[PDB]
Image (tube, coloured by chain):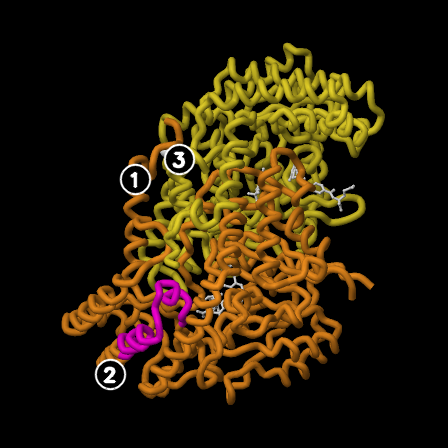
Chain colours: A yellow, B orange
Amino acid sequence: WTGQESLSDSDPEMWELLQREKDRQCRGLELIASENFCSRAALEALGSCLNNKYSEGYPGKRYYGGAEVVDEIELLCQRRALEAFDLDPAQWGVNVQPYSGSPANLAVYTALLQPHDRIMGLDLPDGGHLTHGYMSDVKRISATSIFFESMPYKLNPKTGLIDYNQLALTARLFRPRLIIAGTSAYARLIDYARMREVCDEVKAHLLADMAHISGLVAAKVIPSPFKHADIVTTTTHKTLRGARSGLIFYRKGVKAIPYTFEDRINFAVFPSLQGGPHNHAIAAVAVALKQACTPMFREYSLQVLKNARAMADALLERGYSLVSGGTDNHLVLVDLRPKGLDGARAERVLELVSITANKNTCPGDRSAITPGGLRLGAPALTSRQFREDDFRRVVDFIDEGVNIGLEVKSKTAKLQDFKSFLLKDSETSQRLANLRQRVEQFARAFPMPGFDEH
Amino acid sequence: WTGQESLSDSDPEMWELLQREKDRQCRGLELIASENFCSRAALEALGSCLNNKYSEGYPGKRYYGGAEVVDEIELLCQRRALEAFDLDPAQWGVNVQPYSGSPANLAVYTALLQPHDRIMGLDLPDGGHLTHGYMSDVKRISATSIFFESMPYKLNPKTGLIDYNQLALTARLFRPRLIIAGTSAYARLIDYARMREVCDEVKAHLLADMAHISGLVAAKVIPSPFKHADIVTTTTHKTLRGARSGLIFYRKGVKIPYTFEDRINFAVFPSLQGGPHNHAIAAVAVALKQACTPMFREYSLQVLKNARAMADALLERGYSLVSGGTDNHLVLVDLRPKGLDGARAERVLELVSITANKNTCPGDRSAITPGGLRLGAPALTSRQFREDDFRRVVDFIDEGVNIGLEVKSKTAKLQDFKSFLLKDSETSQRLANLRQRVEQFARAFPMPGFDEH
Ligand SMILES: Nc1nc(=O)c2c([nH]1)NC[C@H](CCc1ccc(C(=O)N[C@@H](CCC(=O)O)C(=O)O)cc1)C2
Ligand SMILES: Nc1nc(=O)c2c([nH]1)NC[C@H](CCc1ccc(C(=O)N[C@@H](CCC(=O)O)C(=O)O)cc1)C2
Ligand SMILES: *Cc1c(COP(=O)(O)O)cnc(C)c1O
Ligand SMILES: *Cc1c(COP(=O)(O)O)cnc(C)c1O
Ligand code: NA
């Protein structure tokens, strides 16, 4: 035993699973707006000897030796990150160690706040992330709500936009120390100027969490949160198209009397929260950030925008209703209540024909436990060189699933009744097997980033 | 642009840095006891298309579709985890999503404790981990000590062992809800049974954090904390030799029922983490299948012999070992009797391609410069080192120490020592000579992983 044997030779059971997953990614229409396909280049860094190095601490400030190379990788990754978002090294630092996006948010809260200090974020069912503070009527759900005190802000249910007026009204009363501008399920741009005004008045930190839209911001195809935000967190996957990791950007240098974010942020990441960095992820992130700086990527991102509105316009023209009426970014929120269906039903139909989308609770939902809609994203299929006509055809395939769903709803009662009918009625099975086969044939023909076979 | 281009073609700056790190690993004597060299098979899973799949939730209970294969991988990882540590699925379950060891511990704490509830772990300078709670005189350092209330327990400096008697005395007073049995820098076997007695008495959960020893435990070459703990955390790297990632094992079934399963799983997701890193989960599954083999038992036996051999060789050269020796994968050297400290020895050794880390000696305070050195066998044993090779590692260390002594007699401060090693041309030649001999020696041995990166 050397540990140089191949995966295919040494663990055939696992190799076959990697192949089935690769095949599933190739044959499918991936419409989850968080999802993307990482480059082979970055996957080579991720699957490297960099996994073997413990480098607790920071460049030049390590707790032990042998980190000279790993130091250059970290410092390179930082510079590439600041470059990717057109940030001045004098006015912005960045931490590249967070293990994912959720750790990155937790680290900011523990860096800047005391336990039980107050946080405001977009409510989860209005399109906020778990890590922005989310608790239910029964219990505290996100650890953000356990260790800190979160009150959500909300959508104006008329417009489907962020009710910025209520946020200002309500932040005056709640007195948050930190307010979060960022979304998991929101088709429009965030008014970061208006967020900073609220934050300036109530004397809160503004945290922009651009996870979903970080690629679009780097490419400069939407306006940048960095103009108005103190702190920016993000994933390195999603629209940045990297390996799974996280980043924390923070302002540094002179405020008005210096900013004091850098030392607090870095300390919270290590030694407070994390152990050894995942230097392999850091390197794959650096690879992906270089790719993000190129004109290729600006074109990718522009196509992401165009593909999204092509999907929107297409859905409007098949008569579907959209939350907020459309999109200014990489996704579309489809309200299926005005079509006489819901998200739960649509999802399971779409799934069975290799179309993968996300449920979305919409403003107009009459039932709190059945989501009304669906999030549909461009980035993943755009990375497979999809264009407007290809997304029109995606929308076309979706419409068939919806229409099966509508037909199965009137021949069923409950939601578990719905899902069993999809499996056991031969006439429904066959129409599903047919649509699936046509979807997989359509999808397979497009190129796919990464390795050929895993 | 396809995203199918190779790394060497598309990003030569990064590919050159990967190649330097690979050469550094190949030419060095890696003695950091938490280090190991991950198999190629596992790294192929790590750098894979499994990076591309969001699968928030758990097998059969995901928040969205497309997870048929990812469910199978996660479920397979769980089966192999329970297999590696010889656990009955009726009595034990396992969560495979923690992003690393430190996340695994925070998730256990948020599952079982309220904010500000009480925790006890081995003090950091006595050999515990940051995540077991750590505060200086001046401030709270570990998040474990911010969100929870940490009080450490200590070694008996007389024996270098954990003072189980003072733990029992002091836990009766402090009333911890959770006590941690596990170490970063400790050469001996933990008396888990005694930890369990103290826990039962004060009505506290016993957590074994076995990160350093997990592979030894898997191979059944040391006693298993699973006989006595309710919860067991571990890294998947270190002695398990997998990708960086974490595990939380927990009791289930009866004694009426255990309530860890749902609380642990919920703490991991949705409370703390987001989407799991399925690529790491697959790498971990690969390393766990390796961990069940007779090969791995032979490896883990060898790690013990190699550490023994390193200890005996150090003793025969007149070095002091904290606790007198070792029953595990590492040895703790006390260099004060020799006239040198850990900070000096660490830096000399680093320059001759031997990586170790400094270690506070029992009875000293963090403020005094650490008197010792932590030396581990797992990494080099993965490169097929045997007992004679570790004797030879100790020869090289002895030269390093002997140089450090000469430089100490010619320098005043520590910063003085450190730039005398660089600028004084006679000692830098003596170092360059040793470095080359060390690197020659080390390069001969095989290395797990890919050839060039
Ligand atoms: N906008 C948005 N942000 C997000 O972070 C996520 C999404 N959507 N969608 C998918 C996933 C879901 C997160 C998530 C998990 C649990 C509960 C929850 O309410 N759990 C309670 C009560 C459930 C019930 O009423 O039956 C529980 O204790 O089980 C809510 C949301 C993550
Ligand atoms: N046994 C053990 N467990 C561990 O988890 C680690 C080790 N050793 N060794 C390396 C690293 C050590 C982490 C670590 C971090 C901060 C301080 C600390 O005391 N910080 C104070 C004052 C220190 C000083 O005066 O230099 C501060 O400045 O906030 C100590 C140790 C991780
Ligand atoms: C997806 C996301 C995150 C982080 O998710 P991880 O799975 O932890 O990487 C954080 N914030 C927002 C707004 C997100 O959409
Ligand atoms: C190394 C270690 C950890 C943490 O592992 P990371 O992957 O560095 O977060 C936790 N506990 C113990 C006992 C360890 O040795
Ligand atoms: Na590329």
In the rendered structure, which amino acid carries the disc numbered 1? Ser
Left or right relative to A323: residue A217: left
Between label 3 and label 2, give the one nearer the viewer. Answer: 2
Between label 1 and label 3, give the one nearer the viewer. Answer: 1
Q: Give the residue pinned by disc 2.
A: B409
For the residue with label 3, is its CB less than 8 Å from the closest atom of ligand 3? no
Spot occupied by residue B400 in the image (x, y as percentages of width and height):
27, 75
Numbered disc 1: what chain? B
Please tell me whether mark 3 sits on a helix, a strand or a loop. loop
Query: Are dots 1 and 2 in contact, CB under 8 Å?
Result: no
Against B12, is B450 above or below?
below
Image disc number at residue A86:
3
Q: CA distance from mark 3 to mark 2?
A: 51 Å
Q: Residue at x 68, y 30 (%)?
A: A359
Please tell me whether mark 1 sits on a helix, a strand or a loop. helix
- Image quadrant assignment for residue B381: bottom left
In the rendered structure, which amino acid carries the disc numbered 3? Asp
Left or right relative to B139: residue A324: right
Q: Residue at x 73, y 60 (%)?
A: B252
Image quarter where the N terminus of chain A lies is: bottom left
Residue A8 within the segment the image draws in magenta = no
